[PDB]
Image: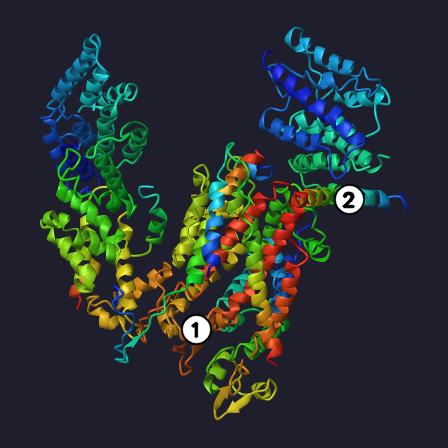
Amino acid sequence: PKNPDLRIAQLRFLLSLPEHRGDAAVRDELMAAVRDNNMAPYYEALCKSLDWQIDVDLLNKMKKANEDELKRLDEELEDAEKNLGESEIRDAMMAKAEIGDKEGALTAFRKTYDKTVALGHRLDIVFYLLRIGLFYMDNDLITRNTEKAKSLIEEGGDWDRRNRLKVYQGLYCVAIRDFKQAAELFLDTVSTFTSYELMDYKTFVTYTVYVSMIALERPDLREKVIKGAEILEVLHSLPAVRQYLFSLYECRYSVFFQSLAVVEQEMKKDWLFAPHYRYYVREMRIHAYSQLLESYRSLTLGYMAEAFGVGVEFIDQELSRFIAAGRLHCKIDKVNEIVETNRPDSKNWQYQETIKKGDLLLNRVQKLSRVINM
Amino acid sequence: EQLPESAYMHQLLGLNLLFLLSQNRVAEFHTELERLPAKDIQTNVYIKHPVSLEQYLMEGSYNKVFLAKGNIPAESYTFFIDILLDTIRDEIAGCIEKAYEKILFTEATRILFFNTPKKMTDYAKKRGWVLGPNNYYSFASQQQKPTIPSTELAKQVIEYARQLEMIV
Amino acid sequence: ILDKKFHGILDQGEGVLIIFDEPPVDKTYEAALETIQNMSKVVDSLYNKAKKLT
Amino acid sequence: YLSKIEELQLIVNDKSQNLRRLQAQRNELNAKVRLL
Amino acid sequence: MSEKKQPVDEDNWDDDNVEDDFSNQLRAEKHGYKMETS
Amino acid sequence: NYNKAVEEEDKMTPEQLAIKNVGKQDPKRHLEEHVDVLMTSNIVQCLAAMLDTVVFK
Amino acid sequence: PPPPPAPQDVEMKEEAATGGGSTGEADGKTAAAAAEHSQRELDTVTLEDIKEHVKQLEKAVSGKEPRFVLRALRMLPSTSRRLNHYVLYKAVQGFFTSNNATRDFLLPFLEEPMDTEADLQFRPRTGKAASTPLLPEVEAYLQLLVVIFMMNSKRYKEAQKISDDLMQTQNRRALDLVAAKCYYYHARVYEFLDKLDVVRSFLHARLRTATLRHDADGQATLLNLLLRNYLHYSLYDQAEKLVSKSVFPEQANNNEWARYLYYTGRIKAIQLEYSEARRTMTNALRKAPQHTAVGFKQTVHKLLIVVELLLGEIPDRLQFRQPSLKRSLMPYFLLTQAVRTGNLAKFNQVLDQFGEKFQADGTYTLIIRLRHNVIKTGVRMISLSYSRISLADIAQKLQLDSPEDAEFIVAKAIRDGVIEASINHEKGYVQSKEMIDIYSTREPQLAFHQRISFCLDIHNMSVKAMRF
């Protein structure tokens, strides 16, 4: 049941990334605390957001409710293992202990991993470790648990749950700058309709496109977005980035820049991207310019400055620092405003890699085969 | 080393350094920057002025020469700054058209100085130069026009196959 | 052109398009990729070496 | 000392004679494989 | 070994080298405000 | 042309020389029988490269 | 008294190998070097440098050095009974009372293995008897009643130079192997107090005596000593390497040569060089032996890639960064950030912020050309960028304010030879070009001679290594 707790993770990100109205973080943390016993939101807001303007006792009462809850959980721990349970005593205690403080976590994972017995004992354990990680912007939890899973969960698994583990892997692959294996693991589209792991299938589409407009080269672009009309029956609900992708074939750079600003702000205000979203947009820029110049040579940026908006000075500094970033072999001027189609690998590079590696590894093995004697 | 502090210490280093700067050395400059480094940035204008002066010389200004010559006698660095004028002018003899299109009378007047002696005329009649019509060119092609890359590398193939022979 | 439907260079500075494509080089592609795989194999053998050493 | 050092080091260079022992092993292997 | 004088002495971390390479370009509107500049 | 097609199978032998712990009988000592041929090939290539400039003038 | 049995065990395991085994490996052995116990003993010296050596404290005081230095005798085949003496003296530390007989009573203890009997003939036992006691004394340099005794113990090691020079036989492939280490510790203890003055002539004549008769691991190591000597102090005798470049052994210890090329890379870095210095820094970098020694590559790498910082074509260097080096590269991280930035006020404000750590570097050569490096970074970037740029665009993009110093920049860049860029001479206004269609076919196969001739060199080297 991590979808609402994924929304709570987004609450924590709102507490983290936007410090505009810290009461809004206090707002939804108190809203998640007044019911569902969720006190961890309340300590979380106490720390980063406001210091709980009025929640000294209004949430300490529900903290005492969580205290009685945890104490009766740990009492039924012995009341039920009094009876025989096929690791199901510890299974129930780990499930119910995955609400209040990290007390619930330490009575959750210290009582499952020791007697995790079958696929489900770790199926839910790894799903909910992914959730306890995703509440913050974690990667140790949400993939170390996948390591345990590889040791524990699947072993054949389901045609349903294993696709879910793979979609977890892809969900972090888009959370991190792993701009391909997300869409690879999000290539299912027949096994992630709706789940307690899918906070929103439309948000599934968001994470998917925010890795597919990069992983999917033009053939894979049309393969998954266009051809794969399975996601289209659902991405019919978010036409902004969809039409962006539509232009992403005809290469309409004006609307490219419109939606580029749009998605830039969007990522600026979206989870698990705050300290990294910098490249994606300028990467889209350079990649599109690549094909645009690849059209032909005797062309101008000014002829494209229209598509660039008023992009003469914009792209001046832009492509200056981009070629300075060592990108996109091409030619362009100011007094001449050139465009180019160049950089064939089978000119020298397809022959330069030869020594690039047969000297790197050559001397690697050389010194490696030097200390064999000296 | 525990001697009374030397009077002309500050500018004997400067005499040596400006002589070095005149004779165009490449590493004794840096062993000079290593033997006494701590008195170079804080003080010692006889050294502090030549080292940042060298930064300005290989920064791109032969006019900081004259800005500086505003005040550098410095007890008879006059001969050495005359040799510094000489290393201005023969480095102009090199760097006047290294890979330039063409200059005219006025860029001679800017980069060179002393508007027209028989010395820039001596340049035009001493380096193998065409004094064009109020105009300059290195030559008619500037590069002496820079057709068999095959047979020398065929001899290379001879000794190359030879060295691949006698070994296994 | 972007989808290999056309292979060549157009023009607006001269308004004159020119077509060209001669991709296939089995020598470079084939041999170079085989050598890449050879590099991977040598990387593999490096550990046999480092093991039998110590 | 004066004229007594170099040939001792020359017998030391019979590691090249040990190289001949190695090539002897080699040609042993080869001759007997050819016998096979 | 270190037998010398010297004995005297991915979330964004992966994207961090590019970030310091991004530390010189409009870190993250004037892009979009340039639309109405003309 | 066939060299790029032949070496890529004997090149699978180091993948089979992945016999790390204790797994290696005869090493499939067939890594040769292509090199010498390659030798001859580019040998003659260089030969003819010579003979061109040599004979032609 | 239960832990000192571990030095009791490793001490006997050391001089069993060293004394008996390398004496039998000296009697008739060493065809090239059959003294494998010499490298075994240098492994155990690294093992005593990992651990405490033998008796620094070890819950007692001064047990082994008064004990085992007695009675070697090398006689009739019951000298394993003298080894039995060595073994069964070990009831003193466990059972009896320990007493202090090191660092003061060692002065006749060193003369005991000579005054017992005419023990044997070879010097590696003498180098053993003056090294294996006295190297456990050097790494405690607390400068109070311990460093004058390192001083006198290495005066006995100067007597070991005397008995290396006049000992009657290639025992230098044990004694120079130990003497590399102990002469580094000589230089250490001599320069924990002052610069060494006549130890320079000690080192000179010690290099002289190892010239041809026994030229095995002595010349290169004493030359490392001499090089770091001329490195720590004023810089006058690098012309000695420029006139007497005899620096090419078998490059035996495989890390000695690596750090040797590092030190002479610092030399050519401080003489003047970019290219050759950065390539020997690169070769020493990739010739880092392992990372089995914690954070010792790190400070020395901070001073290694100063020349790559001086290239200007370096990104942030973060893949090397030890997290314990981070609090010391708090200047150095912002310094390579100031390499990536073209700001002038930040170029001097990093200096104004971190001049003390720049003095800890102590290399003015970086800042005397790092401004010039900033303008060369600018010219490389922008001259690789545009075909026919103007000098005014780049000039008043990098705050040059006039045409004629931009002309001197472009002129000294042609003189430094990066790009073709000329001047459409009326008032400046550069007319220029890039360079593609330069050449791409016969020019690779020029360098392919060096590629495959280098490959066949390494073929024959693997052949001569297959010989072993």
Q: Looking at this rendering, what residue extends furthest in the top direction?
A: G95
Q: CA distance from mark 1 to mark 2?
A: 56 Å
Q: Secondary structure at mark 2?
A: helix
Quadrant in which the N terminus of chain G appears: top right
Do circles 1 and 2 both sit on a common chain? no
Rendered position, A304 above or below G250: below
Q: Give the chain letter at badge 2.
A: D
Type of amino acid at the residue the image marks with label 2: Gln
Rendered position, G257 above or below A78: below
Q: How was this image coloured?
A: rainbow
Residue A37: % across, % down:
12, 24
Residue drawn at (41%, 76%) of the image: G432
Q: Nearer the viewer, residue G140 or A82?
A: A82
Q: Which residue is mark 1?
A: G437
Q: Which residue is mark 2?
A: D17
Q: Secondary structure at mark 1?
A: loop
Q: Looking at this rendering, what residue extends furthest in the front direction?
A: D36
Residue drawn at (28%, 18%) of the image: A115
Residue G182: % across, % down:
69, 34
Q: Give the chain letter at badge 1.
A: G
